Length: 81
Ligand SMILES: [Zn+2]
Ligand SMILES: [Zn+2]
Image (cartoon, rainbow, N blue to C red; front, side, top):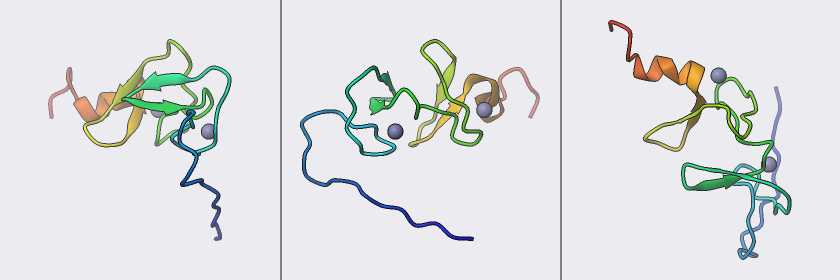
């Protein structure tokens, strides 16, 4: 298996860039977890489903993001354990 891709400016930090790609944005964006992302890059870490402006996202105590349906396992609220 192979991978290895780069291109992330160190300099030029005035505008806003999707945290996930470091590329500059111009149109609409989403804000959560005190970060910034392209409207196409705010997704459940594990499953990759794109979250939209209203779909229930979930945050973790660490740099991670999940969907409300699946973060359900990390909380176990109405379950036994
Ligand atoms: Zn992006
Ligand atoms: Zn999910």
